[PDB]
Image 1 (cartoon, rainbow over the protein chains, first blue to last red):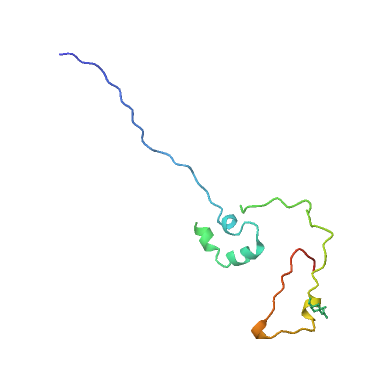
Image 2 (cartoon, each protein chain N blue to C red):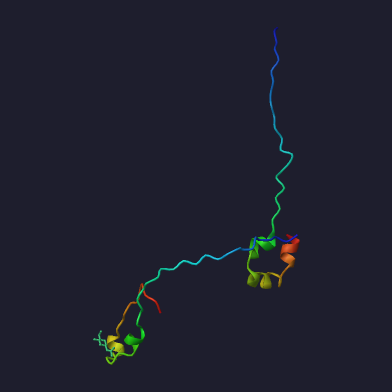
Length: 48
Length: 49
Ligand SMILES: *[C@@H]1O[C@H](CO)[C@@H](O)[C@H](O)[C@H]1NC(C)=O
C-alpha cells in the first residue's frame, strides 16, 4: 500500500597496478661476477 | 633499458690506531713444543698482524 526508494552500492575490480620487474637488477644488481653468470642464461630474464 | 647505479665519488676508511702487535711468530717459534695429546691454544685479539 505504500512504498519508498532504496539505494545500494557495488564495486567491481577493473584495473590493476602495472608491476614491472628488472630481472637483471633483481638478480645481479651491482655485481659484475654475477652478471657474467646471469648472461649464461639470459633467456630467463628475457621471458620474464 | 638495463638498470644503473650512481658511481661513488670518494672513499671512507676508518681504523683504530695505536694497537700492539699480535706476536704470532713468538708463539709459533717457542722452544716448548707440545704433543697432540696436550696441544695448546692461544687467542689473539685486539692486535695488528
Ligand atoms: C715460550 O713461551 C713461554 C711462556 O710464555 C715464555 O716464558 C718463553 O719466554 C717463550 N720462549 C720463547 C723463545 O719465545
